[PDB]
Length: 178
DNA sequence: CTGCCGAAGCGAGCACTACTGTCACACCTATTTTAAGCCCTTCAATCAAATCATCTTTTGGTTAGGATA
Image 1 (cartoon, rainbow, N blue to C red):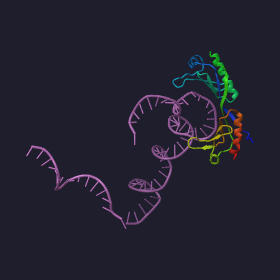
Image 2 (cartoon, rainbow, N blue to C red):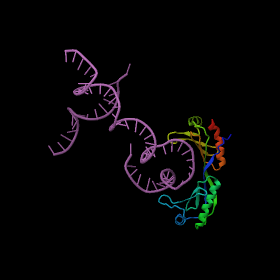
Image 3 (tube, rainbow, N blue to C red):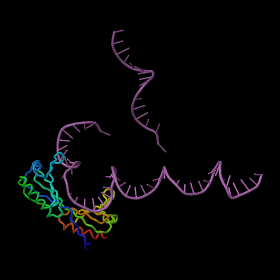
Image 4 (cartoon, rainbow, N blue to C red):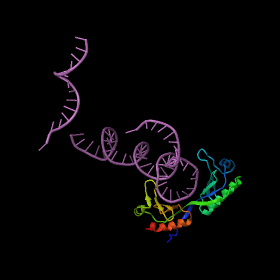
């Protein structure tokens, strides 16, 4: 059963279609929050604290936002940037909101001997202590990629909802225990 | 007044990896979030090697406990 520690989400990734053409130079000229460094990259990157997130905008009318701790928080930040662009003088719309990725982490509070895991799980676990200190495991159900360390803490990514993170956590937990 | 054919020296066949005309798709980086491990600096707290001050062990000379020659 559960060890009493829940996987806390660390990140959320989401995108929405603004539905109109925008001028990045105009945004950099008007908005009190903007980049335009075309010498490096022709784009504008936002960020707000409530929710704590970073978003990025193009002239093509797409938005990519990331940084929240919950999917609904990410959507709130997305709608905040949509409001900002609407009051920037652009006819922005909050259309086709899609959630792309999230990151979570947890712990088991006992040491992990990676050698046994690689010896019994090499077919899906990649161990290489020379470059990346931890161990890499790719999980199929659901499409999750997992990082495991000796300290017992685990990083989970590749899901679309917190339920997937929890379910993968409890799938791996017996393996971590033994 | 023009023309044939020999003598000797040449030759062959057998021994139970350099550029150029394109072209699309790679190369390239705009950022988010971890979990333990990273390189270099850079100063600060602690340390230990070397040097200075002084007590003491002994090597040449004076003193009065001590003695021969």
